[PDB]
Length: 49
Length: 49
Image 1 (cartoon, each protein chain N blue to C red):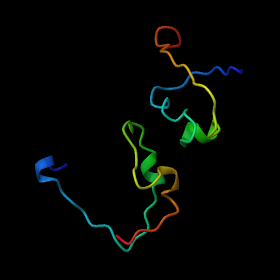
Image 2 (image 1 turned 180 degrees about the vertical axis):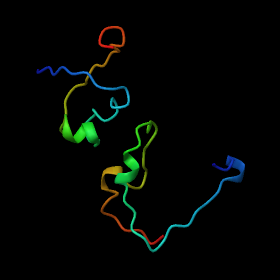
Image 3 (image 1 turned 120 degrees about the horizontal axis):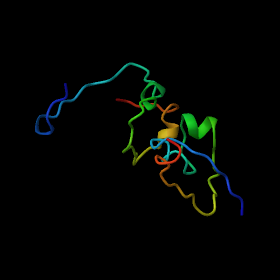
Image 4 (image 1 turned 90 degrees about the vertical axis):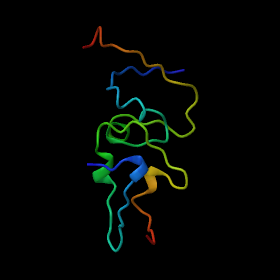
């Protein structure tokens, strides 16, 4: 289940290492773009939160 | 000018463009960042499928 847009939820992710390879594998990705980063270089970056 | 012929899925048309990566974009065909020109894609559901 996903919450409605007017009641959009939010989950906190911290103190863990995330792999985007298990994400890109999804076939029906149609609209995907990034502003401050590039998807090809998201596997070698660190984030405070 | 050189011509390369192949048939791909509909979901993989976005990865053909240079600069993008993927399962087909990295293991089957890749284009240089300085690619000159354009590709042409048309449906072959009538013929290939």
